[PDB]
Image (cartoon, helix red, strand yellow):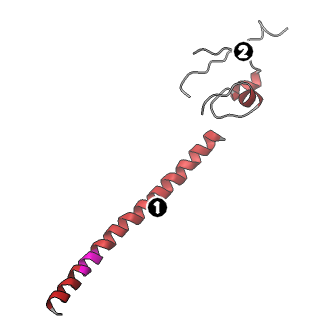
Amino acid sequence: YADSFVIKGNEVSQIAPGQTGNIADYNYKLPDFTGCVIAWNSNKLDSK
Amino acid sequence: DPPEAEVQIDRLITGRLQSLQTYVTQQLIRAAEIRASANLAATKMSECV
């Protein structure tokens, strides 16, 4: 699979198995997981 | 957290598994000497009594 979504910079750490938070618990929960998590900051295309 | 708890639970599972094995291993050694003293008491009963 390939799940693509945009999250805040300080919330990227929450995209990981077993973590808790606004993003982790109510928006995207990873299983407590085989895979690779990729995150590159993108402010030129999103921030305005 | 679930990842932090699973790390510190295996310390209690491994700690108590070695606590049960150390118990059962010693019971097997004790029961080997009770059987030795129970084979002797059955010989005394057959021959002395």
Quadrant of residue A47 within the rendered picture: top right
Q: Which part of the image, by quadrant, shows the N terminus of chain B? A: top right
Q: Is residue A7 magenta?
A: no
Instruction: Left or right? Give the position of A24 relative to B30.
Output: right
Number of numbered discs on residues: 2
Quadrant of residue A37 within the rendered picture: top right
Residue extending furthest top? A45
The magenta stretch spans which residues?
A: B33-38
Instruction: Left or right? Give the position of A29 relative to A33.
Output: right
Q: Which part of the image, by quadrant, shows the C terminus of chain B? A: bottom left
Q: Position of residue A38 (x, y in %)?
A: 62, 18
Residue in the image at 68% along x and 34% along y: A19
> Is residue A45 positioned above or below A10 on the image?
above
Q: Amino acid at mark 1?
A: Ser
Residue in the image at 51% along x and 52% along y: B13
Q: Position of residue B15 (x, y in %)?
A: 50, 56
Q: Chain of mark 2?
A: A
On the image, numbered disc 2 is attached to which residue?
A41
Q: Residues within 10 Å of mark 1 (few under 14, many from 20)?
A: few
> Is residue B26 positioned above or below A43 on the image?
below
Q: Amino acid at mark 2?
A: Asn
Q: Position of residue A8 (x, y in %)?
A: 77, 21
On the image, numbered disc 1 is attached to which residue?
B19
Q: Chain of mark 1?
A: B
Q: Main secondary structure of the magenta part?
A: helix
Circle 1: element type: helix
Residue extending furthest bottom? B49
Instruction: Left or right? Give the position of B7 relative to A14.
Output: left
Q: Position of residue B12 (x, y in %)?
A: 54, 54
> Is residue A25 positioned above or below B33 on the image?
above
Residue extending furthest left? B47
**Gap between marks 1 and 2 measured at Cα:** 50 Å
